Length: 144
Image (cartoon, rainbow, N blue to C red; front, side, top):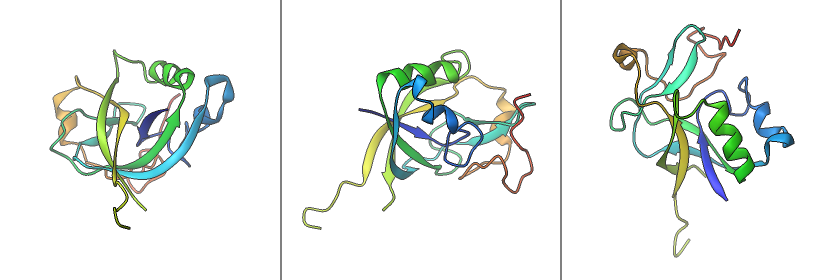
């Protein structure tokens, strides 16, 4: 299967998690708790307080998230859920698995939804290692 690393509103406990569990969309199975190997800026921006993984690897913070195994139906759904390619783009990155001889692999390549073109000042907004709509910043996700 394809693997998707989710860092935002699709995570367990977050406002859009349900779309992964709606079987009309295909299938998504939790595989691992993960953390990016490379840092990225993850910022809450815009009137809706959406989380954006800015495509600036090498800056920001290591980002916490969840790895899901998805079928082709669910990948096509999620591409459209994320308004690709105009808003987000589906890119790849390597994720560290968070859990003897030979030792277990500790990395896996995943797809992720990142954003390449954005207001430049967004890069100076607070950087998040773990997004939560209900987190300490107070900027609750606002789709309305």
